[PDB]
Amino acid sequence: ITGTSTVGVGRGVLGDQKNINTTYSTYYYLQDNTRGNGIFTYDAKYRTTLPGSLWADADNQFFASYDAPAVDAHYYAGVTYDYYKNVHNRLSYDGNNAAIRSSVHYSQGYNNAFWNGSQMVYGDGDGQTFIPLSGGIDVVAHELTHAVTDYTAGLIYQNESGAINEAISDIFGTLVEFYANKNPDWEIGEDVYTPGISGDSLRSMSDPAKYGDPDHYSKRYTGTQDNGGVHINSGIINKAAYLISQGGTHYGVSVVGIGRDKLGKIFYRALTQYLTPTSNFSQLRAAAVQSATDLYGSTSQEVASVKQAFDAVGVK
Ligand SMILES: N[C@@H](CCCC[NH3+])C(=O)O
Ligand SMILES: [Ca+2]
Ligand SMILES: [Ca+2]
Ligand SMILES: [Ca+2]
Ligand SMILES: [Ca+2]
Ligand SMILES: [Ca+2]
Ligand SMILES: [Zn+2]
Ligand SMILES: [Zn+2]
């Protein structure tokens, strides 16, 4: 909408106060004009028609319980935009400052979130498996990263290419969580999953097997559930990424860690320069090796660590 840029204040899903960029024209709208062609947050009003209505508020204060998922979807989309721009020199998900759109209050008791090809969508959860899913910065950044993948490598969402697609979203979701630097970890979804259970999460990158996901190619899932295991076999790649950054010895193979920033540079370059829609795990290894070679040189520790990490998870 046409209006003037304003700054509202509200409380997110976890009870934290934050400022949000809004637009004033009669109402205050969740429309942030400070980033690219805008970040726009919509109310789906417990239905499944998308996007719903651009979020309107009478007073620019967003402290109602109903407001909290919208505050966080809007704010964390901004953090994610900032990460890609500041760290990778990428302007929005398409590289050309495309508007970022999110809808909250999708359906009733909906225990998921997604990128639908055009926008992000967040359920409220049922209050037991999940609370509103936009409360997790790693979740928001995971979903927006699917848009980045859409516009770059285009990894088909099935089998190994789909597991890479998922792992890319978990990797960058985690790197955005570290960028914001509020209670960062190598777990996925911990802030919004199972409010009655402390210390759990949806997936773990540091130890995928904690939640039943493979941490070695020999343990990959080969069945048809979950589009051929895209959220299961992602553990093999998540573990490799964790090892590249943090180091460790895994099934007897030692990896020298090179840190999160270099992990992000290597995988961003692989995603945008080398991966294709049909890339498999072996082709990801080759893409990561070539990316690290471009950035750091063939004789570098960074290249050696990429190779050790893929060896450790059984990907040749
Ligand atoms: N986002 C993942 C994990 C489940 C999230 C809620 N059931 C999926 O759609 O499979
Ligand atoms: Ca208000
Ligand atoms: Ca109010
Ligand atoms: Ca965390
Ligand atoms: Ca996390
Ligand atoms: Ca929990
Ligand atoms: Zn997903
Ligand atoms: Zn995903």
Image (cartoon, helix red, strand yellow):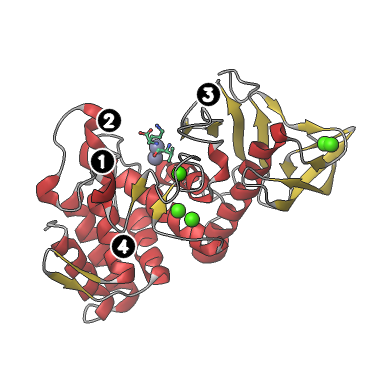
In the image, is 206 to the left or to the right of 142?
A: left
The disc at residue 172 is: none
Q: As shown in the figure, which amino acid type bears the numbered disc 2? A: Asp
Eyeballing the image, is 262 above or below 41? below
The residue indicated by pointer 2 is 226
Viewer-closest of 272 and 184: 184
Q: Is residue 183 above or below residue 74?
A: below
Between disc 3 and disc 1, the foreground one is 3
What is the CA distance from the residue labelled 2 to the residue labelled 3? 21 Å
Mark yes or no: residue 2 visible. Answer: no
Residue behind mark 4:
242
Number of other residues with Cα within 10 Å of mark 3, as a class: few under 14, some 14 to 19, many 20 or more: some
In the shown orientation, is residue 19 left or right of residue 295?
A: right
Mark 3 vs mark 1, CA separation in Å: 24 Å
- Identity of the amino acid at label 1? Ile
Amino acid type for the residue under numbered disc 3 = Gly
Label 3 SS: loop
